[PDB]
Amino acid sequence: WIREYPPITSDQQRQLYKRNFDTGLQEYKSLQSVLDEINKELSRLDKELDDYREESEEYMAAADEYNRLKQVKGSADYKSKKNHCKQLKSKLSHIKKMVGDYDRQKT
């Protein structure tokens, strides 16, 4: 993304990069939150499974729900969000680097 966000040469450009970095960080946190919540839900169900008797109707219900979330985690939509997350982290890291390079160069 050195092409979309090249080395900065003006203060207005710096401000645009900051505004876009902020929007991207909001996007990143949103995606990350979905992945974190899926894992939190799996952990709650893991506790339920570890507690309920294996032969109970309750264990069967928890197992069904747990397996649905594991199906989501192994799904393409989940894989895509995780990938979008990584690419956004990369893009943001780059924008931050450009802003830092500029601020040092204007010192």
Image (cartoon, rainbow, N blue to C red):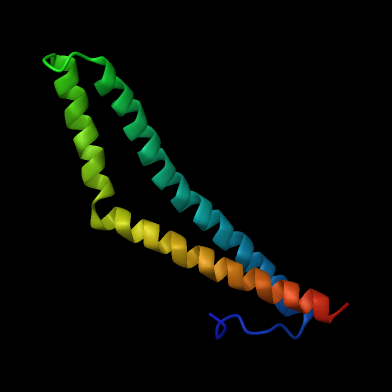
Give how far across and how far down residue 99 sits, in percent.
71, 73
In the figure, residue 48 lies in which quadrant?
top left
> Extreme right residue here?
107
Write the residue at 25% across / 22% down.
Answer: 49
Q: Is residue 65 above or below residue 76?
A: above
Q: Residue at x 20, y 36 (%)?
A: 67
Answer above or below: position of 16 versus 42: below
* Residue furthest to the left: 55
The quadrant holding residue 91 is: bottom right
How many numbered marks are there? 0
Tell me if residue 82 comes above or below residue 96 in the rendering: above
Q: Residue at x 40, y 34 (%)?
A: 40
> Which residue sits at x=22%, y=24%?
62
* Residue 26 picture location, percent across and down: 56, 54
Relative depth, front residue between 50 and 18: 50
Q: Is residue 26 left or right of residue 15?
A: left
**101 to the left or right of 87:** right
Quadrant that contains the C terminus: bottom right
Q: Position of residue 32 (x, y in %)?
A: 46, 50
- Determine the image quadrant of residue 63: top left
Please tell me which residue lies in front, 16 or 106. 106
